[PDB]
Image (tube, coloured by chain):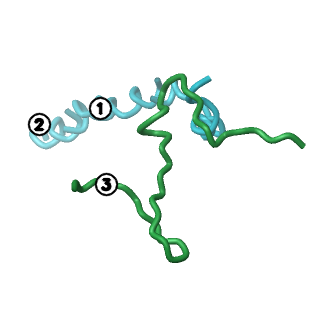
Chain colours: A green, B cyan
Amino acid sequence: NARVPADLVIVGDKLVFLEALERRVYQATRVAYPLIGNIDI
Amino acid sequence: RAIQQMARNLRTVSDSFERGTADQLLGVLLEKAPPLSLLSPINKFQPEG
């Protein structure tokens, strides 16, 4: 295994990664960062 | 009266550009940078396009 810097938040009873990959990946470029979808009302 | 009166204005009259080197780097560092509310979505509306 290898040590890696990342943030881990405990919610409820489960330790989950809290990844917001917009900086390392999808950056300064031409790819659609998902999670910005649209809704129709 | 010849010894004391040019050590205080070439000590204070040759450090004027030592009153010169902070106000010409914010007259284009404060005359090449305007206003704010739009930066803030300079990180909420443009990575891909």
| SS at circle 1 | loop
Indicate the position of residue A25 as horizontal and vertical percent values.
44, 35
Instruction: Report the chain holding disc 2.
Output: B
**Could you tell me which secondary element the residue under label 2 belongs to?**
loop
Q: Residue at the location (61% across, 34% down)? A: B35
Q: Is residue B10 left or right of residue B20?
A: left
Q: Chain of mark 1?
A: B
Q: Of the residues shown, which amino acid type is indicated by label 2?
A: Ala
Say if mark 3 contacts mark 2, CB within 8 Å.
Answer: no
Q: Nearer the viewer, residue B16 or A29?
A: A29
**Residue appearing at x 58%, y 35% in the figure:** A33
Q: Nearer the viewer, residue B20 or A11?
A: A11
State the image coordinates of residue A11 (x, y, percent, origin top left).
53, 71
Q: Residues within 10 Å of mark 3 (few under 14, many from 20)?
A: few
Q: Residue furthest right?
A: A41
Q: Residue at x 86, y 40 (%)?
A: A40
Task: Please state which of residues B49 and A1 is positioned toward the viewer in this rendering.
Answer: A1
Front position among marks 3 and 2: 3
Q: Are marks 2 and 1 in contact (CB under 8 Å)?
A: no
Displayed quadrant of residue B14 = top left
Binning the other alpha carbons within 10 Å of mark 1 as few (below 14), some (14 to 19) or many (20 upward) gives few
Q: Which marked residue is nearer to the observer: mark 2 or mark 1?
A: 1
Amino acid at pointer 3? Pro
Task: Residue type at mark 1: give it.
Answer: Ser
Quadrant for the C terminus of chain B, please.
top right
Q: Quadrant of the N terminus of chain B?
A: top left
Q: Secondary structure at mark 3?
A: loop
- Residue under numbered circle 1: B16
Chain ID, mark 3: A
Crowding around mark 2 (Cα neighbors within 10 Å: few <14, some 14 to 19, many 20+) is: few
A8 lies above or below A38: below
